[PDB]
Length: 87
Length: 53
Ligand SMILES: COC(=O)Cc1nc(-c2ccccc2)sc1C
Ligand SMILES: [Cl-]
Ligand code: NA
Image 1 (cartoon, rainbow over the protein chains, first blue to last red):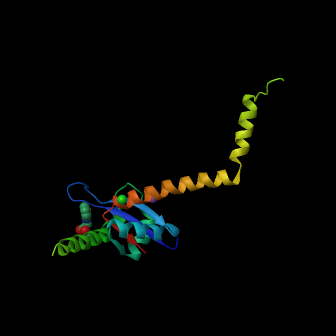
Image 2 (cartoon, chains in turn red, cyan):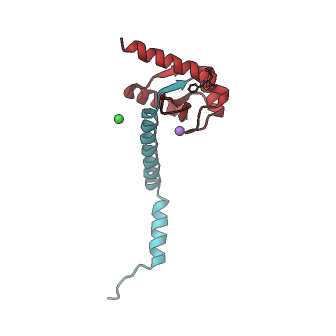
């Protein structure tokens, strides 16, 4: 592909591990971007991780182990942004 | 006059011909695209974050 967009779900006390919710490529990525902005879902540029999840990740499966370290950084960033935005 | 009658076979043939129509094929594709758009909105709403390249 040229463009990649991958959805990740992680809610502490609900999901024991993070889940892959979607995988889109190319033409569908601009559409995903619009809907994410409209729905208040954060969209982060992580070129190595998006590329890695493109090859390995399966929709409605847990994030693979090969990407959990890189995913945990994104998740810890998202939690820090959430707590800070409450100020 | 003798009453016209479409056989079960004629009805199937006329309908298959209709399914071959460019306008009718286009509407099927359009319907599939609308379900994909709906699914895309639901997939995004179910997510915590989106990672992009
Ligand atoms: C970079 O984070 C770690 O030390 C790795 C790790 N993260 C895990 C995890 C589980 C649930 C949510 C987010 C991360 S399990 C596991 C062995
Ligand atoms: Cl909505
Ligand atoms: Na998908």
